[PDB]
Image (tube, rainbow, N blue to C red; front, top):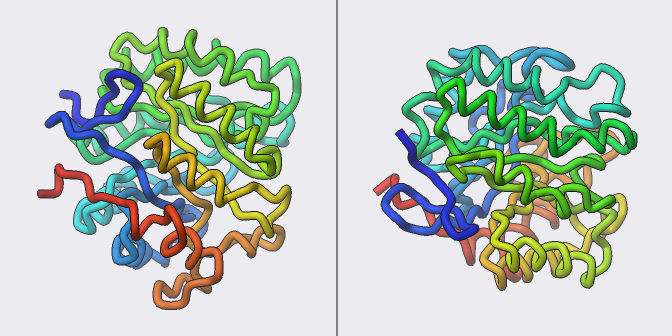
Length: 302
């Protein structure tokens, strides 16, 4: 059966209610001991958590019982669970990265824990699946279409979320200009594109151009990751959040806590303590166009 699905370029629950994602990523794979994050993220108003998983290619694989637990924690905390395979990051440039086909192999291994959860779980096939290597970026559309087709043939009916090349930032506009081909490859239409906005998006005009391209064409889109202006590259988070609100687009900030050395400024809370927000946590949850003021829980929980 289908649950979350796409119609007219937007994301809807099975009952016809539009769902506008307002959440954050949680680094589950690297911090398996911090499963209190699910409740904490909901307590600040989020309606979705993007969960970092591994297929085992680069990090330690999250097995079926672990993923079942994650899904149960999302559901008990009334959060839509967006699962993502992080090992694909930077393929073609990053040494030892997974392909999208290897991510699909892993999703198929998890089939029994995912089927029946289409109202609650979104499958983000692979994080930022290409780096900047030209020959592999050129395969983004055909590799992504192939991955979607494999999932559909394996019986998956969930809405699928697909990331862009160029480390998710699509500065070559490959996803922008070929998303129509990829969307066509999913006969169900239950595919959503996800842009990651970091340093490429320090200018408001570039942000607005990108978001409006998708809205004007009816190409479903979320801002699946974004940072703030004191961060590497200086993304304009005020514009990202304001435009997402104006255009009624989902957004997911990076990240709850636990950033490694280069991106500690992207921690929303200090050391996974939900009561200790950083300035970034305060900004994304409680500032203008923030999660607490704009987010609505998915109606499936009622």
